[PDB]
Amino acid sequence: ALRYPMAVGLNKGHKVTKNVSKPRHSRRRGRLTKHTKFVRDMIREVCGFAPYERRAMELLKVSKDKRALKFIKKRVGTHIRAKRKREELSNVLAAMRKAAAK
Amino acid sequence: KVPPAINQFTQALDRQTATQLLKLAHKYRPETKQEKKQRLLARAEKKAAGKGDVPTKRPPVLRAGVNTVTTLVENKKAQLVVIAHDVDPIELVVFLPALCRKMGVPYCIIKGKARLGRLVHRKTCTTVAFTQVNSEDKGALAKL
Amino acid sequence: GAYKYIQELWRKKQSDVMRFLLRVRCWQYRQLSALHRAPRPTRPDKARRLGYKAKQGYVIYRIRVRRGGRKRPVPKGATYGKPVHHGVNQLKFARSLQSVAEERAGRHCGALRVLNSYWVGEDSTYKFFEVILIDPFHKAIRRNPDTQWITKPVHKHREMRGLTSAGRKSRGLGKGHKFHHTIGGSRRAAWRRRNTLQLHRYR
Amino acid sequence: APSRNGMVLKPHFHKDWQRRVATWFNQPARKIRRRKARQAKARRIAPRPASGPIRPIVRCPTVRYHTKVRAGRGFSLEELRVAGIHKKVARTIGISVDPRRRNKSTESLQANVQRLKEYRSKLILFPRKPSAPKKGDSSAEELKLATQLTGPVMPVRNVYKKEKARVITEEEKNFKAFASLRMARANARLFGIRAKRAKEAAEQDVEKKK
RNA sequence: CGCGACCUCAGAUCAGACGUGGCGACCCGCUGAAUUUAAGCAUAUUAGUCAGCGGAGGAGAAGAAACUAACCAGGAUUCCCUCAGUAACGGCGAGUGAACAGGGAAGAGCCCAGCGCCGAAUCCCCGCCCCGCGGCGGGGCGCGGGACAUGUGGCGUACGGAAG
RNA sequence: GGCCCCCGGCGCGCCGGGCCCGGGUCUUCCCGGAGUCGGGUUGCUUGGGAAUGCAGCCCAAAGCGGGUGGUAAACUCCAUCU
Ligand SMILES: [Mg+2]
Ligand SMILES: [Mg+2]
Ligand SMILES: [Mg+2]
Ligand SMILES: [Mg+2]
Ligand SMILES: [Mg+2]
Ligand SMILES: [Mg+2]
Ligand SMILES: [Mg+2]
Ligand SMILES: [Mg+2]
Ligand SMILES: [Mg+2]
Ligand SMILES: [Mg+2]
Ligand SMILES: [Mg+2]
Ligand SMILES: [Mg+2]
Ligand SMILES: [Mg+2]
Ligand SMILES: [Mg+2]
């Protein structure tokens, strides 16, 4: 025939019909719920911020974003975790900026 | 330097107000073991002859316990929350003033977890919450 | 739902409120003895997460351990041998300090069973842990299924055989490619299997 | 010392091996003890199959063994759900279940539901109280038809679809098997770099005129 | 300005229980050499072994995936055969050295915390009565004590669960 | 093969009491373990090799997150577990 199943190539593999199904409930782990988000927001305004988080906000306030990321990565430890933390710290700065605007 | 989350529990109710609050709260104490037995036996006697189920309007009662009160505040079901000022592991109630204010339920801080315990026939209670109240005490609860 | 708030609160150990509480408590624990019974769990949510229940038979012991590594206990630093074994300082104990605190609680209270432990504070020179113990002969413990397992003879001194959560972490147990050292139950179990010469009857 | 030609040998006998030597003089005794336990277990579960629960049809993982099929740990919940068996009742009637096994394809799914439906048809169920047969089975098909089953229940067997000889068409004769394999390997190897070069060329194309 | 509640502590030859020490072939947690080999020797090897300390049971430990894989996918632990003296480590020297898949022995799965709902529904102790003794339980009673809302019990646990 | 004595677990009728509703469909809700993970460094350990595991010290999390995917790193998709 023109084309055959192959053990190599971009479309390699034995051909089976894929069984589509709902993902397992363990794969749901880590999703943020409405109540858990509410609790974490409660604790954040009760507690505040860690001293390194406040320092990183000063760097973001003067728009030293590369230096802020270097500082956060040195504190938290990894690039992926630092990028997520920097976005959140940028978000709270923007949130309190528009709160003080009105 | 005590952070305001911990310093807020030093502001307790004055003696006059705490007296009106506990005097009202005396009318809604949870039923003891003895009078629950008396009530349950009466239900058994009445069910035997001859009314039947007879819910008979489960009366308003003072809800107690930090886990119970927290859910009531989160559901906006509490009308008034009373927090003891001397919870020794002070993490059980540090969020409650902020949580109550966020949910709009009025809250006060009172002197003595032992006084709250006597309300519920126990040694100690962190918090008690006022749910719906009898009509003759709606005026009193509103003033508080 | 208050336990959820306390859990999120204790995840903020560097906040102003938690920094104050941890410092004051660490000062207070410094004034007490190294081994000391606590009237109640300091962290009730963390305790019950680890197996504790507020009923008779469960007791709490606060343990204070000294921080740092393990100096080799040789006279004048002389470890007579090859230079690879000359190390005296910068040596580290195989078991964590939490496992040591559990062992000290269990040794003192030999009639109780160590269940778990958790962190309540630390200094530059001390770490403080609270250990959950169970009285195996109290009727509340003994008449309850789902708790009767701790009453068995095989479960005595778990903290000394590395069977508690803290003591288990140093044994290198686990599933998959990172934990090939302990296939068979332990390092010794794996080592004996891999170093035994199987001489069959028919070779 | 080496002596003339020979193989460079590396014995692993430098580690006090004689303290850990496993002799096998209890091998014949071990086989007797295992046989006795098997026979005692079979007697204990008197009409139930001696080998145990039915096992699913399962393909072997890697590329070395994926042509073979064997018995798995237990039936997946997706298989039981479409076969109409409760996941908690299945273990009572001799069906092994594996809650952590997934079904990636439908062929393996449907292969195992015919296995469950075949087993369920061949199952003789005794009533809990023999004097009160509620919904299990008739007494006729369990008075004498009940017999302990020896060997695995419905043993998993590799099957081959025999192809009859056919006339080779011209399209099959013109197919280039070696050339296709060589080109398929090249296409998979250069797929990522071909896209990047096309992407870079597209960037130059959308601004080439200015 | 004494009397109460709680908290945190203390004493008792208080009522009732429990631990200690031995054995230690097998098992678990640590600590841990040097002889030796390298034709010297220091890394390496001996060896995570001897010695040392602690803790168990009739077995122990492990154990129901923060797994293996990359397949058309398998599916807790433990043991045997094989993988394999292999991948790898190594003054890349002497030497050391697993795992996956496959075939078997055996095969068994579950429980909390948390989120919630249920008038704390929960548990221990002490007196009284009856049925029993043989490892001390069953039932009933006590406006009898205590624990416990700083959280007991029932439902329920990632395979989803609850309520209509 | 016989006789004697003792002990233990198997079905039936009864006894004393407990014992409380299961599945499918739809709808509305609810879902998780923190000085822990992870990172740096140090020492030991491993076949684990730009670091397999364990531990001390310092830093110190997130929630479409986290871990793993045997070469360090950035971006991207996927797989797998929790
Ligand atoms: Mg050496
Ligand atoms: Mg006495
Ligand atoms: Mg002993
Ligand atoms: Mg030599
Ligand atoms: Mg020599
Ligand atoms: Mg020894
Ligand atoms: Mg065991
Ligand atoms: Mg275990
Ligand atoms: Mg699981
Ligand atoms: Mg070979
Ligand atoms: Mg070695
Ligand atoms: Mg078998
Ligand atoms: Mg509960
Ligand atoms: Mg790579």
Image: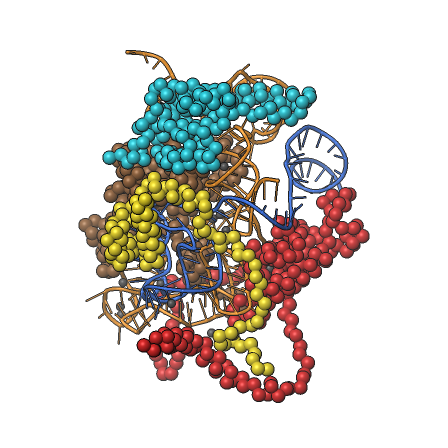
Chain colours: A yellow, B cyan, C brown, D red, E orange, F blue
Answer above or below: position of E34 versus D210: above
Task: Tell how many labels.
Answer: 0
Q: Residue at x 36, y 35 (%)?
A: B94
Q: Residue at x 41, y 34 (%)?
A: B104
Image quarter of residue C38 = top left
Looking at the image, residue D106 sits to the left or right of residue C34; the answer is right
Q: Is residue A72 visible?
A: yes
Instruction: Give coordinates of residue D110: x percent, y percent.
Output: 64, 63
Answer above or below: position of C133 versus E143: below
Relative depth, front residue between F21 and D131? F21
Relative depth, front residue between C101 and E142? E142
Instruction: Give coordinates of residue B34: x percent, y percent.
Output: 53, 20
Relative depth, front residue between E159 and B97? B97
Image quadrant for the C terminus of chain A?
Answer: top left
Looking at the image, residue D112 sits to the left or right of residue B114; the answer is right
Q: Residue at x 31, y 39 (%)?
A: C18
Answer above or below: position of C148 versus A53: above
Instruction: Give coordinates of residue A1: x percent, y percent.
Output: 59, 82
Q: Is residue C114 visible?
A: no
Relative depth, front residue between C83 and C173? C173
Image quarter of residue E91 = bottom left
Image quarter of residue C109 = top left
Instruction: Give coordinates of residue E154: x percent, y percent.
Output: 56, 37
